[PDB]
Length: 57
Length: 8
Image (cartoon, rainbow over all chains, first blue to last red; front, side):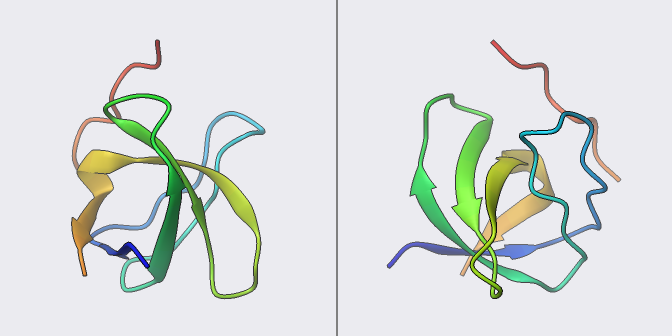
């Protein structure tokens, strides 16, 4: 699977966004854009996440 | 935190 680690907290701006906290491990599901990817959190919730806020895991 | 990138 493709996983990333949150480098900073992200509160989410649009309703499609996936809010997260620094340290969270997220799984990448799709990359419809270069800097915005769809990911899933440890609870199974899905949403868009900003690439600059994460590092590869 | 870093700048949140624009959407397209």
